[PDB]
Length: 623
Ligand SMILES: CC(=O)N[C@H]1[C@H]([C@H](O)[C@H](O)CO)O[C@@](Oc2ccc3c(C)cc(=O)oc3c2)(C(=O)O)C[C@@H]1O
Image 1 (tube, protein in one colour):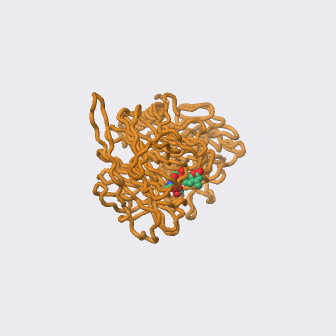
Image 2: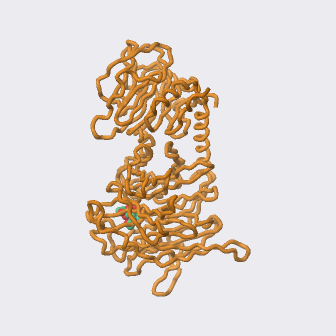
Image 3: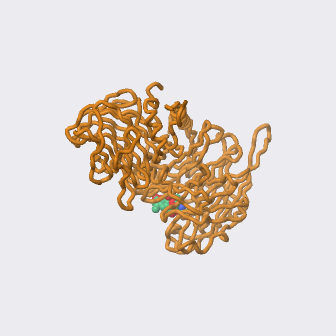
């Protein structure tokens, strides 16, 4: 939890009471565990919805949906049960409440089970299941000089009539909301990303939406891959972005521009960025994923635990900030090594809050955190992004002013700032590690065996912000070679392995003063010529499985070659710059590199021309 931030235990395990209703009688009843946080703003009234697991934290046990609400930004709260279960058996339950705010209404979607003690995805049929929508109406009043609110919860209505018996190549079984907070789309539609099972017990995600304020519901025709559960969605630039849980695998993210009729994996931006554990081989989690506007910039906030402990412990809740280009780790929201899986982030009246789980010995509370420190960090980072984009965009490039330097898709930039061991990203997301480097204007001068910089891709580890490069990228740099090498030496490239010896696309230079562009594992043909001490502009592009190399804005002869053989997606380890940065590779590149730009797409001709012409105007040195 950041400096300046604080929290309280809001839903207190084995302590907080809720009004338990049974057979016409209501009693204040202590709850064992509270899980499944959803924290929202209903026109000024903060509402926290969760599971109240009365007797045990076990999923298949007695559970009602509880709500706490506050008209004073969380200093005090009132408590009620928003939805009660059927009371059919000792384990009846309403589960995984998923919330949408619209007007003064809360729409809460829950699965309902009567008596099964088995996890829902293990059921062979729907005998124990129903899917219910309950609507809470929030009313505001000003009694006794001060503001008051109340919420009237309607009786739940079953939406089972909207679930078809068949979907493309399958027979349907059950479905649930994705948990947490869902959305109202820019067209007014209520939009629940849902997790669905078929009769083969496979799980997949769909879009379940209503065009009439929840009276009737439809499914989008498309779906995620099998294995994608607890989907969470937001709307971004006219499309739904659906971020999914995949147990034992990296999270998949899809985009849909047609209410779920067609799903496209977001390979160029967010898909496969987030891993559920250090080795991405453990259960995943529910995630808060929202689009907000902070100081005028639309961005997305995303949370997920790091899960160093493994299994479902899910320690180390982390918050991430992205503008769909750069991906910044705000940091850890939970405290120390506590188990802290599910979460919900709310941005309200320029203050940031998080309602999230803490779990000790399988007893769960929900803490309510005031994210003061994190918002300060976010605002600082957003200012940097805005300032560097403005700087670049405002440059008058050589003709009159020619076309502007492009910042669309610009993800990282290594320039003047560097410490003894790192080359700093101007965008503050991913630095490069360095060896044998001396600082020069807008870059670094390298020498010696082991020299160079490494800008990690898969080497980022659990969370791989540059995963997009496996699909498309442009890497740009200005370079100068200081010594003629003994053989062939590296200058810039994308490596598939940790050593640099297995390349996707790279540029080397040799003892005969020629360039050696390297296309995958293809035989290298030296070409062109360079002069010692002369500055050159280098561009490497890859898209559509094809790599190209440009020197001074022009392609090398014979460039535009296949660098991804076969159907497998590359798994780039890192970009190397100015050497391999590997003391085990015997090369010694004596070179200076300045202003390394990384884009998440293949730049066009004009954009490459502009960068070449403007190469002496883009550095961060004077700023
Ligand atoms: C309807 C329902 O079962 N929802 C639960 C959800 C769900 O089981 C998973 O997404 C798998 O379908 O997992 C959760 O519950 C689980 C599921 C399984 C386990 C297991 C197997 C061990 C454990 O320690 O905690 C668990 C917690 C989860 O925290 O991931 C939350 C929800 O309670």
